Image (cartoon, rainbow, N blue to C red; front, side, top):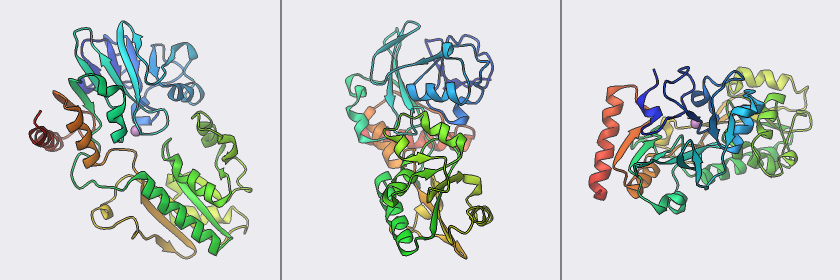
Length: 341
Ligand code: NI
């Protein structure tokens, strides 16, 4: 049944709750972003109101075929009334179209639901600075001190320098980047830009990217693989067997593959810096795992929460085990005692 951490008290609302059938008492279903564990259950047969960003609404219409009459897109950073309740959508710094949602309950309680987010100091100057938040529904994906990772900027700088050097040494090297969802577009776009190429991809992935309101996108992507030297493939294909196979398909246009796998976290983050990352190599194929994250590090999470000073925290990730729940509750108490709220 629908878990309590997906329900907004004092309202008829649910967040990211599309796989339980009809939730009794739900008058409006919000969707924070277009990732499959969050939209799981939506289709052209859905007949309840869905509230979301413009970009998420484009993907619902074009990829899932939800009918336009049930899609209610809202602008960001704007006070809106939904079924009698004031709400605001804020940028979550996750994937394209991802939002956090501020609910202003009739009784005076203010609730923030982060959806999935990568906390950032710039959030401390949004509409969040303007009033107190009592309850926080928090993306706790990486809520443990082992989880450090570099800035997105540092990671993109590494990828751009690595690719440019490789291709300039060998003009017959192909660059491949893995994907299985929206998000992390900066990785393949930044590499293609430094190489003066468009990125080539499947028709299904091209359709997906044309939903994202990315400026000048027609100048940056293409379905013509032959004219491109940065290819996107399914993340499943980013291994030696899949890459050797792909190389055969290019008809001797290329003699070397340099591939990127933008993982979340991996245990080499506890030891190694970004400047010191190395690939796995077999023959003329090299695979780089790069720690490009669209979720908060532990320290980024902690700074946001200690700034916001909520009265109550409700985790939305890692909630399935008692040992995980208890560990998270210990960190929350540490943070509150350190900061004095
Ligand atoms: Ni997500």
